[PDB]
Amino acid sequence: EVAAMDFTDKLIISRPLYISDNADPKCGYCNGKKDSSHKFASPGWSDFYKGDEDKVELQSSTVGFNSELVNAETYDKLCNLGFRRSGSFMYKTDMLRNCCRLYTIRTNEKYLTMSKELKTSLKRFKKKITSPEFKPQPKYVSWIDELCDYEPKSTSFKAVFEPAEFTDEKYDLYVRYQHYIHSDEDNTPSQFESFLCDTPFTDSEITGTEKEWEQLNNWHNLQPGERVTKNGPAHECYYHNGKLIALSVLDFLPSGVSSVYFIWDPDYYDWSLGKVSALRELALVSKIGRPYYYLGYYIDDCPKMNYKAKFGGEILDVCNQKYVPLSKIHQIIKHNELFVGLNSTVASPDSEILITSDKINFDEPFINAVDDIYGPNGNASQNAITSVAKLRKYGINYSPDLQRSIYKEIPNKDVYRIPNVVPGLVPLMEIVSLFESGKMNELNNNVVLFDTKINALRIVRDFISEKPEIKTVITDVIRLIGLDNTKKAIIII
Ligand SMILES: [Zn+2]
Image 1 (cartoon, rainbow, N blue to C red):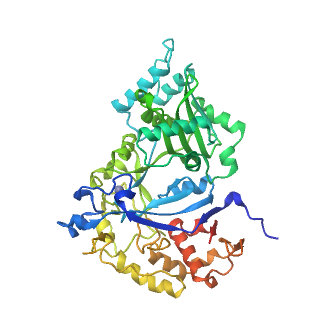
Image 2 (image 1 turned 45 degrees about the vertical axis):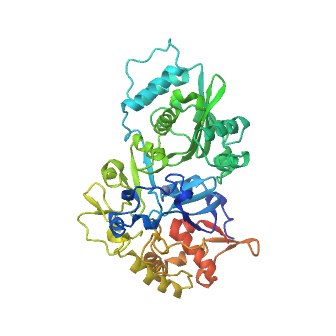
Image 3 (image 1 turned 90 degrees about the vertical axis):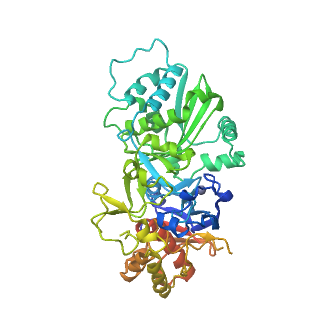
């Protein structure tokens, strides 16, 4: 006998897509409009195009895959690889080629600086919901403890955690909010359902139990060292005298909480709910004893996204697979640069950084090595073209990227084709090593396919003998999520 397939431990995904189009209009953050000093990924590319910035057509570019099943531990890993979910679609930008530089940001109460601005938003909230008879304690150790004292005592305000389920009330509020912010989307009931209610998580992570939701809704009273069992998606409903005035869509992960989406009643602009809800969610992360609050993507030059910097924290270096505090690099990403860290005591990189050895230490001095690796005279492309040829010998249908520039120039597409060189994907030279060391044989008896032809699941038994189209899809999944995660995948082909 062999153990039944355990779908509490599987990631079911479609084959990867690489979607690239003109940033005007595809990019909702910049609309393809950038100052020429923000237009490129590095000073080396800025200088390569100095004087002809107007002959590049910026592109908006995403790579990812649809998910039919993911558990919270696996989604946590994907967040910490630089992915985000949009409904059930797991994606990231191509940070080398995209118009805007999107960084994965995370923070917590240790990073947070309670500025006058943030303090004012909490003070207003307290005044909106708190009776004049409330008597505060003479001292609160943290602003979190102050909030956890008065908020549950309000007779007019109540926030409720519940499963992420459609209601007419929620949808009507979303329509009004999306119109107030000038969403250029349909915003039909089905779209709201797929975006913010239906998810690829396990049923236990979606539905939970009555005890789990009651425990979560008691969070204001959690004591030090106490924890909650909840993982997976949730809605937090904000009620003022029985009326829904805001809805927070959140994912509970082993390492903390991710903010999916926040909507509020435009008539409540004077409650500062955008800032208040972020502070409440930071307080929640602290009270449930988890380390990080994830606000999604940070774009230093987009006002709709750089508000996240006010809560502090650290930014993911996808090339090193480590976080660096925002305060240490903010000055060198202010012109939409891509950052690739390298300790100053380390020789100039001869290649893309190996996602295998001696990790970067951001507590030691470091520099941005982006142009050594990915600049117009960097080494990444030379190494990738040589790897493509070796990989073709294993039946991997990759083609070499031979163009001089990573940018689209005025002259004066296969959605299954990923570029040879993408920051944060496994470099092709490392993919070669996996084949040459036999580490790719770890896929045998582990990775599973859903063959749409025969309409059945099939465990892969001899990877190298699979058809090239199949081997190529699997290898692209490895580039995106790594070998260990792919070994727990069911890939739909
Ligand atoms: Zn953009």
